[PDB]
Image (cartoon, rainbow over all chains, first blue to last red; front, side, top):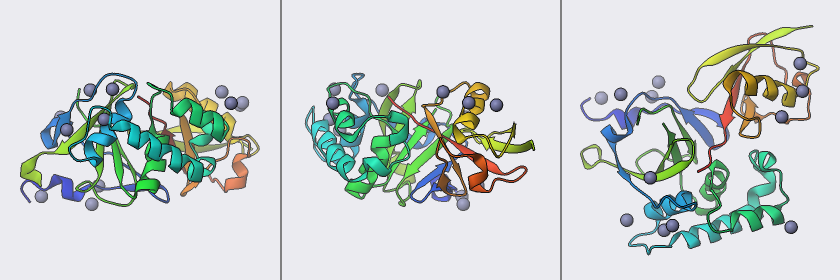
Length: 162
Length: 77
Ligand SMILES: [Zn+2]
Ligand SMILES: [Zn+2]
Ligand SMILES: [Zn+2]
Ligand SMILES: [Zn+2]
Ligand SMILES: [Zn+2]
Ligand SMILES: [Zn+2]
Ligand SMILES: [Zn+2]
Ligand SMILES: [Zn+2]
Ligand SMILES: [Zn+2]
Ligand SMILES: [Zn+2]
Ligand SMILES: [Zn+2]
Ligand SMILES: [Zn+2]
């Protein structure tokens, strides 16, 4: 059909609740890029942008608080926790520090804690992969753009696609 | 006895690796790190929906010739 590409994304299971896709498209053909501050909190700024209506400049602190709560429940069982290599207490001290980069590990934990679905699109703006945490689809997902290997922005589906 | 398996990267490209079932997951990660040019603490592996644990031998997971393992990126920013 016309204009319904996003309705047919194919997600392959990685583990229960995490999926990957490899659609071929340019991000800006389907999404508005909502640019976030370049500081080290950009991951949490991006989540806040898409989950907290009429937010404030540093609404991301609430998301980091939710990350703490999530980590206390889930960190020891996250496969990416093993890559970080820290005890829960040392992880929390690092994670809660100003400007400490967020990641797929916090996305995984926040999807559980908040009940949301998060998709990180990694990229030109030519998509290489989407990685999805949670079982929802792209239309109610928190869509993030990961670019330059080191930066997050928020994405919003363009109106003509719904 | 040596066998070939496949490891699929983020872009969806599979590459072939010669392994032994006695070697560890960690050592397979070192081979994948060399081929893909990504540090071994920036990805983790799965097979058939199960995370692969670094210290365990590959044979604990029932890999067979040309089994596909996923290389799952850790993305930070
Ligand atoms: Zn169509
Ligand atoms: Zn489909
Ligand atoms: Zn498909
Ligand atoms: Zn294109
Ligand atoms: Zn940006
Ligand atoms: Zn900021
Ligand atoms: Zn806004
Ligand atoms: Zn914010
Ligand atoms: Zn400590
Ligand atoms: Zn080794
Ligand atoms: Zn070797
Ligand atoms: Zn190493």
